[PDB]
Length: 66
Image 1 (spheres, rainbow, N blue to C red):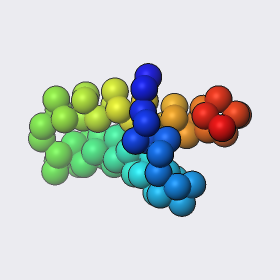
Image 2 (image 1 turned 135 degrees about the vertical axis):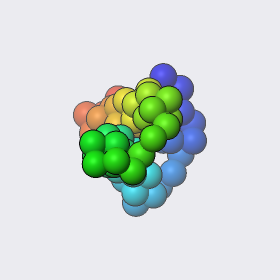
Image 3 (image 1 turned 45 degrees about the horizontal axis):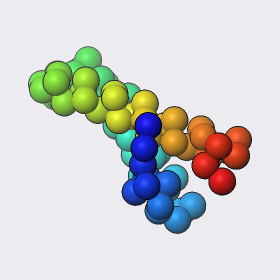
């Protein structure tokens, strides 16, 4: 929902952060699916914020976040 911070970065920072969340979720599931990642609460938290963050990027694409 709210950001400030996650919309407040510059377009170059914003991508480089919101990309990081979007990848991280997918890479963390990939680390488990191998056998490296072990804290699954961290993944589950990481999804909430992946979803918020990767939504922020979406919202910024159409004009919802100027």
